[PDB]
Image (cartoon, rainbow, N blue to C red):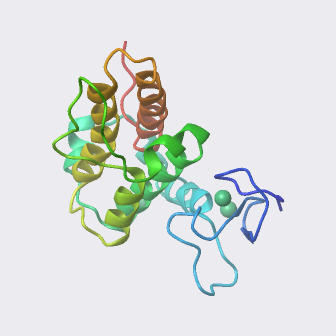
């Protein structure tokens, strides 16, 4: 197994996966690492298995169809994974915790959002469809863009959104286009 967290790339108190070499801190894994379960499989492994069990799930889908899906166990897991994929980028630190807004010539967003809030929402099963999750994720980056305006810091929003969007298209096998 690995000696650093797959998500945050640090050593510490790690829990090792039984079916692959990855390792995680307890609250870096999504969901948080389970109390017992021997063997244990991580979220990467559990996603692999869904794809192997249904090979045609990798065929192209329309975004619109994927968003209307109900949050049944397998879509809940893919959303969890997609969220984990964003936390794997170090720049996620700017979007993790609750923001505040006091900049000359800007107003705060009507609906603030951050990664840890979406984590808690997924944890508490507050989304009934994929759409609710995706909307809150996009809202994070949209809020950033509108607030920081021409300040070059807006680039951080574009960049982490791109990681979100790429992984969205991969996990949910969105039809490739030109
Ligand atoms: Zn970690
Ligand atoms: Zn694994
Ligand atoms: Zn099948």
- Residue 154 pos. (x, y %): 40, 23
- Asked if 141 appears above or below 33 in the picture, the reply is above
Q: Does residue 19 appear to the left or right of 61 in the view shown?
A: right
- Residue 92 pos. (x, y %): 52, 42
Residue at image coords 41%, 47%: 57
To which quarter of the image does residue 25 belong? bottom right
Furthest residue in direction left, as rendered: 110
- Residue 149 pos. (x, y %): 31, 20
Q: Quadrant of the C terminus?
A: top left
- Asked if 6 appears above or below 138 in the picture, the reply is below
Q: Does residue 103 appear to the left or right of 162 in the view shown?
A: left
- Residue 136 pos. (x, y %): 27, 47
To which quarter of the image does residue 1 belong? bottom right
Q: Nearer the viewer, residue 60 or 139?
A: 139
Q: Nearer the viewer, residue 98 or 48?
A: 98
Q: Does residue 45 appear to the left or right of 164 in the view shown?
A: right
To which quarter of the image does residue 119 belong? bottom left
Q: Where's ligand 1: which quadrant?
A: bottom right
Residue at image coords 84%, 59%: 3
Q: Nearer the viewer, residue 53 or 177?
A: 177
- Asked if 148 appears above or below 167 in the picture, the reply is above
Furthest residue in direction bottom, as rendered: 36
The number of numbered discs placed on residues in the rendered structure image is: 0
């Amino acid at each position: 197994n690995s000696n650093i967290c797959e998500v945050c790339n640090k050593w510490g108190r790690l829990f090792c996966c039984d079916t692959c070499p990855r390792s995680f801190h307890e609250h870096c894994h999504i969901p948080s690492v389970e109390a017992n379960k021997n063997p244990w499989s991580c979220i990467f492994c559990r996603i692999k298995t869904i794809q192997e069990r249904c090979p045609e799930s990798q065929s192209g889908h329309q975004e619109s169809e994927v968003l209307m899906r109900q949050m049944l166990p397998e879509e809940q897991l893919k959303c969890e994974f997609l969220l984990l994929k964003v936390y794997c980028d170090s720049k996620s630190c700017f979007f993790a915790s609750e923001p505040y807004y006091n900049r000359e010539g800007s107003q705060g967003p009507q609906k603030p959002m951050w990664l840890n809030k979406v984590k808690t929402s997924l944890n508490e099963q507050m989304y009934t469809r994929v759409e609710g999750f995706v909307q809150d994720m996009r809202l994070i980056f949209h809020n950033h863009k509108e607030f920081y305006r021409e300040d070059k810091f807006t680039r951080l929003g574009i960049q982490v959104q791109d990681i979100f969007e790429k992984n969205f298209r991969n996990i949910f096998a969105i039809q490739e286009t030109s």
